[PDB]
Structure formats: structure tokens, C-alpha cells
Amino acid sequence: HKCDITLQEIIKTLNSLTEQKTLCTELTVTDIFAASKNTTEKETFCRAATVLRQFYSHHEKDTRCLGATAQQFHRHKQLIRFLKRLDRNLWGLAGLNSCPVKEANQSTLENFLERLKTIMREKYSKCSS
Image (cartoon, rainbow, N blue to C red; front, side):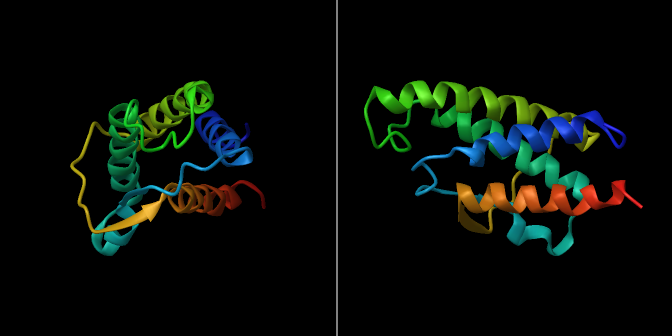
């Protein structure tokens, strides 16, 4: 893209997630957003990125997001892949290495995604003029 490639890829990758999500957000996640009282964009991608990595990785077989039969398992397969691709892009974008997570509140996946999307979309405006 004119702006950047990582951004385009991320947005698209993130889009698909909500583009056809299911019932898995009913679970609670770590809302690092309620901890921006003193942080930066770079740090945000760091934490978030980290959380996402573990979140999916540690949730692989939690039998909490499934709520269904092997039906989800297959669905998750693709989803997980998408998550890895995204996180991977976010981690690289961070422009650093890694940072600890400062738990503060909880959010339903859907919210987390929306928030991230909004941010990306918000800055995406700095492309046209």
C-alpha cells in the first residue's frame, strides 16, 4: 500500500476475524487498554501482542472457547493461524522486543478486537490528504 504493507496486512487479517466470527468472545480477556494512563503506541502493541500470543497459544485446548463439538476445533484452526499472523505483524511493528502485561480490567474478545481495529483505522486516516 502507499502507506505501509504491514498495516494493510494487519487490517485485512483482523477484518476476517470479525468478518465472520462466532460465539467465542463470551470469555474474558486482558484489557490492556484500561492501562494507557501512561503508555505509548509502541508499548501498546508490545503488551497486546504478548497477550495475544499466550492467549491463543495457552488457550489452544482450554475447552472454554469451544462450547461446541469438533466443529469449532476446525474453525479455530484457521482462526488461530490468523491470530498468529496478526500478532506476528504487531510484534514486528512494535519496533522493539517484548514487554510485561499490566493487568487492570477485563474485556470480551470482540471488544479487544474492535478497539484495536479502531486505533488502526484512526491512524489509517493519516494516509490521505
